[PDB]
Length: 124
Image (tube, rainbow, N blue to C red):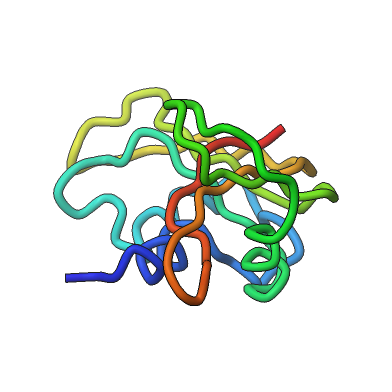
């Protein structure tokens, strides 16, 4: 199994690029991060900032999660992100994604010691 923290890193972190490199970015990343294995994960966001900067969000603006949980945090600053969403004729195992680049505040839920992100809630 995966720890919640490692799963967040696998699904949501891409510090290797400043932004999506092409229209094919989500197709490549959704596959290589193993998010199309058992099904097409419908929606998923990658953050193009350092892991340290994203972990730091857990000490930023405490806000409610979409489901009412109280352990969500919004980044004080905007961050480079890419939204990946199933589109077109996406049918498992032929998964297909729309790549949408943006600069937005991220909202994550945090847990544990160290207190680190364990769920991507939304971006604003």
